[PDB]
Amino acid sequence: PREVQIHLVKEVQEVYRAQGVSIHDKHIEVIVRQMLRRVTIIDSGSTEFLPGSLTERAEFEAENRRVVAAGRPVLMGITKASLATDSWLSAASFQETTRVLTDAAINCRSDKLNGLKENVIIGKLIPAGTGISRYRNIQVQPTEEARAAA
Amino acid sequence: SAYDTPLGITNPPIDELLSRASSKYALVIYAAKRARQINDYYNEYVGPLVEPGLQEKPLSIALREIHGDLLEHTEG
Amino acid sequence: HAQNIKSAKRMVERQRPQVWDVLEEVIAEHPVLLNRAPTLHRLGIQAFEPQLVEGKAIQLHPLVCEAFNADFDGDQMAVHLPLSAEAQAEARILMLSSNNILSPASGKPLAMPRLDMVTGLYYLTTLVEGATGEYQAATKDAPEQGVYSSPAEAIMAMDRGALSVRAKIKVRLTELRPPTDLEAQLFENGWKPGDAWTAETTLGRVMFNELLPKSYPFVNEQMHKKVQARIINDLAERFPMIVVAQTVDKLKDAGFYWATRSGVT
Amino acid sequence: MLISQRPTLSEETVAENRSRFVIEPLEPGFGYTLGNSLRRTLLSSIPGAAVTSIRIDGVLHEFTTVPGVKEDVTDIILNLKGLVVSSDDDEPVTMYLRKQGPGVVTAGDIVPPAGVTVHNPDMHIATLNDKGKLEVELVVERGRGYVPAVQNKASGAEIGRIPVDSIYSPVLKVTYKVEATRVEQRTDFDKLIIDVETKNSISPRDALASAGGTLVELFGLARELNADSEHIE
Amino acid sequence: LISQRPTLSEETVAENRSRFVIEPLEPGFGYTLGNSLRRTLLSSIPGAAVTSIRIDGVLHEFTTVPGVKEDVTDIILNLKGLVVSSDDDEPVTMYLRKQGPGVVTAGDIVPPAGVTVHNPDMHIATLNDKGKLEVELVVERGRGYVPAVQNKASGAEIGRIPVDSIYSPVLKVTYKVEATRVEQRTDFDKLIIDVETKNSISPRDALASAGGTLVELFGL
Amino acid sequence: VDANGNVIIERGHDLGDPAIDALLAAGITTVKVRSVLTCTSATGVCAMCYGRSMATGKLVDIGEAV
Amino acid sequence: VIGKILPVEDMPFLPDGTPVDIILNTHGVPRRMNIGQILETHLGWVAKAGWNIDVAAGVPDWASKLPEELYSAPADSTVATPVFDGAQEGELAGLLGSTLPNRDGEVMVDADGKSTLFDGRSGEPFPYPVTVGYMYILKLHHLVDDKIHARSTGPYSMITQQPLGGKAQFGGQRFGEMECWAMQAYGAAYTLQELLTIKSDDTVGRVKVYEAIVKGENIPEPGIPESFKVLLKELQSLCLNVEVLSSDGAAIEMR
Amino acid sequence: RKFARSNHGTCANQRPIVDAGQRVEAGQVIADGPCTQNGEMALGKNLLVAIMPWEGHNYEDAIILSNRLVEEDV
Ligand SMILES: [Mg+2]
Ligand SMILES: [Zn+2]
């Protein structure tokens, strides 16, 4: 993964460097991260795990380690990443609504609204920026020395 | 270093504000809640802490009071 | 001014002389969100303080056109009015142009002299030999001729058709913080807010450095867009955003003021 | 005759000698008209005195600094240019400065003849090193604006007599800006803000009063041709 | 210094246009003074221009009169060529009843006392034998330029057409600053200001009106 | 760390022109920077592992939608 | 676009006192790569300023291939130049070098085709001679009566519950996806969530915020967008049971 | 056709150019179209332009007008 993570960023930068525009590697690395952050399964799991299924890292590892599977690193296309996203109402928003929504419905698949894109569609407070619980819940009292002074 | 007398909506300076909160995103709500309070005062229900102007906007009062350091916030 | 809300809603419909004195009072430091479709990046939207102007045109700032990617060849921009205290605040705090000088892409300043201001400041600062009122430093026969006690004296001399704005001249400077080597040589211990020192520059470069912040060291170099970018980037890295946001405004004012007397046709 | 909105004059204080005036609100194109006029009048018109030629006892042809001084001839020149003097002669008044021994040469160290007065005795002119005595003869005269140094066979045939560029102007540095004001249903009414850095000798309101005084007197002759109809304030 | 009071000699090269010479002046002072005068002249001089016209035939600007060559629009655009002069401060009403065949000139108006039209050679409209052109014009005394005030908001009748009123008797104003005396022995500027009017007021009267105006603007 | 171990810059440094120059003057032809590619966050990314923001001119915010 | 209409007087004016009508920016020309307008401008000056060329006793070089009897021309002489068999490069250098005492006995424009302008605003002369001349300019249809549009509130659509599009129906202005992207790039959740609820959709929201603004009270927190009701009802119409659970406890309807 | 609303909203105002006592050949211009003055495609106007930057009003291919045009109605 890491050499490809270098390669993609180098390659994406070189063509900007060529055209004269300059972007900061980390902005590419944010997308290349979003490329290299899933596993393809040849055949493993043995409980609600289909052979030949794209699976998220953290959720896979937790059941894989077995405290009480078998995954290899995969490189996925951005469309194939937004297609194989954890969310459903956003996946529906991108492409092939009926196909994914049918699967979502029978699966009873719960989206957390951690993604911004879904939380745009429903007219709700965007969780990004000024919409995290540490921001949206802030009690601002006037200071004890300022109160009596008025 | 050399402020060069800022005026209007750029007053008070944003750097002197940013220092009070952890990040600007905190400063936004940290102000907006005080703006929401001084909005309530006209109807906590604390009054304008810093000297209010002829027709100064609730926002500017909050930012002036945060610049004066008359408030504290709680990261939820 | 209006006896009843309905009567106010009539008076605003009739657009009577009594509303205009109020609209300044209502628009006083009340931000608006300018957006151009297609919005290609974050700086494609920016918040501003609306000044009230006559005519039928939105008077955009010349520095935010690099960001907006908006040529004045029939392009149109949307304005939005944030209503909630939160929206109004966030408009003032996050997306105010003065705050968003540097690119999210790199962190190079995008709100910088471009097209006109570049030629203006380039003419202003470019030191050209064989000019009027040039500092010669005559050898035993005559005085040095072209030395100046203050920038004021030089401005007085340049207002007369005697000294040209682009010439090697010897000003005595006080309010401008000297170059690192020059401070390191002359003062060492103390700075130079009140301390005086002699330069070998052009009145234009002095008039330009006059725009940049009191404590910032001296340039003594022609303002090529790369050098402007480097200086404004350095200033953005070293100083507060308000300081840079004023210095770039003075750079714009001076830039355009001198873009005329540039003689570029 | 015609009537308009009576222009206000307010005196914003920047520092001791330097100030800003605000003249508002002016009809569409009353800002620049009286603005640049006021600037050029403030800079040029007002009477004041200054050094025109100096003579430091030493240099006949010796281009290098005078032996037994810390400064250079140029530094002495551009320092002396700074010296602010007021003369009521209308004649090239010659005055001598002489000082000896170690330490500083203040503005107070000069001995002014009858009529002339230096308003800052505390300002610095030179720093004299040990085992040395500097003696300089300065020609102070009255004039207008800025005059470059010209050896027009007064200091031409002379062995030395260094000619120096004069700042007669009591007002050192004037700048100005115009701002559009919503006075009524009409906009683009120009509010003249005028930054004015003077010397210690005069007050900026005095300089402005003098400039105005010269301008009203200058336009008085045109005013007094016909007296047909004016846009009265 | 040179303690000489500034002086200005009133001159003439034509009736419509005259030169003026101001001297002596402070070195580099001329251009600014000339500018101030030029600007005061071009902006703020009280002119007599048509405010509202009234044709009995047509109701509005975008129709035509029976038996005229050009229509009320181009008639209105031609009427702007009037250099009417009005000593009256109030709105004054003139009349024109040119009947039968011929070209209608600016001398064919019948003005009340203290209203004068100074270029009667100009061409307004051509009438055939069939046509009659009856117009009454309203002259008001203003300054600078005003947009054609609406007759809907104000309590004026359908018959009246507002016109683009230009209260500028001055036509062209320039200046050039002669060197006059060499650098040595106290050099002074002399400015020569070329003034060109609409033949409504004499350059002297306009210059005196400007001189009268801006002195009121200058406070001490 | 350099050849000897004369440690010039510690963990949690913004790497400004002074620091970048200092690392060159130290005499090292490589440095290990903390990026999003190696971030052990449950949801999204963690501030310190992104680096300083370009917009702010300071450490990236704990709200930023990078 | 017309950036500024200057009052007649504050306008870069000729030595004879004629103010120039328009000033087109120089930096545009070499970038845009259309110098035509400048040759068109130059020839314009030759067109307005009549030109009795004192040809010569043996003809000047530039007028070696001179066109049909085009040596003299009166004041305001309208000239034809076809789009290939037209006025040549160096011809204009000869055509500007042409005496035309405009009332006064002096030339305005120089051999190069520039003129020394006095600044109406400043009052000073420009320090170098600037390229003045006569240009044919076209009043374009892209008019503010077509383009300018505002809406605080107004008449809404019956089908969608967001303000209309167009000046005829007194519509709003379209807040697209790319604006939402930028709002989110700023991280201005409150602005976007205000734009996408009360400013567009929510029927209680718009009247409540109008009421709250005119009363001068706190803006109510936008709760229930019409879009979400529409999509919830629409998803429930396609036989998908969608129920929003809290962090802990029992689920709820929006109202 | 006196002040006819043309398809694109602009006016199609016509005027006569020729005088009464005048001979006219076949295929000659008699009337004045909406964009003719003596029979010639005249869409816009001839204006005295100056080419230079002017205090940032013309920055990025913007245009500066003299009120004279708006007043004189050119
Ligand atoms: Mg375009
Ligand atoms: Zn991390």
Image: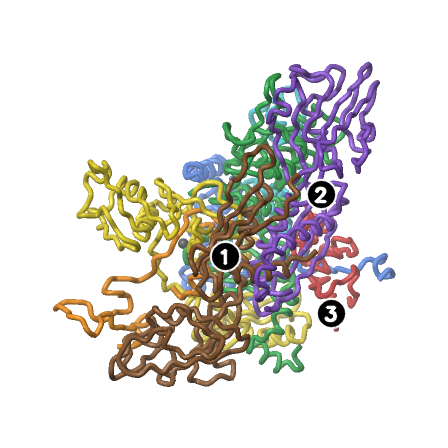
Chain colours: A blue, B red, C green, D purple, E brown, F cyan, G yellow, H orange
**Residue pictured at 83% horizontal, 19% vertical:** D100
Q: Which of marks 1 and 3 is in front?
A: 1
Residue at the spot of label 2? D198
Residue D134: image x %, image y %? 78, 20
Badge count: 3
Determine if the C-beta at disc 1 is less than 8 A from ligand 1.
no
Q: Quadrant of ligand 1?
A: bottom left
Q: Does residue A93 appear in this view?
A: no
Asked if the residues shown at circle 1 and circle 3 are in contact, with their CB atoms under 8 angstroms apart, the answer is no
Q: Identify which residue is drawn at 62% across, 79% down.
A: C8
Going by the numbered disc 2, the residue's amino acid type is Thr
Q: Quadrant of the C terminus of chain A?
A: bottom right
Front residue of C30 and C137: C137
Disc 1 marks which residue?
A: G9
Q: In this view, does D59 lie above or below G134?
A: above
Hey, what amino acid is under mark 3? Asp
Report the amino acid beneath label 1. Answer: Glu
Q: Which of marks 2 and 3 is in front?
A: 2
Marks 2 and 1, how far apart at CA: 31 Å
**Given the current orientation, which residue lies at the most extreme left position?**
H26
Q: Mark 3 lies on which chain?
A: B
Mark 3 highlights which residue?
B40
Circle 2 crowding by C-alpha within 10 Å: few under 14, some 14–19, many from 20: many
Residue D12: mark: none
Report helix, strand or loop for mark 2.
strand
Q: Which of the two residues, B1 or D40, is positioned nearer the viewer here?
A: D40
Label 3: state its secondary structure. helix
Residue at image location 45% in from the left, 43% down from the top: A74
Measure the alpha-carbon separation of dots 2 and 3: 50 Å
- Looking at the image, the residue that sits furthest to the right is A148
Chain bearing tag 1 is: G
Secondary structure beneath label 1: loop
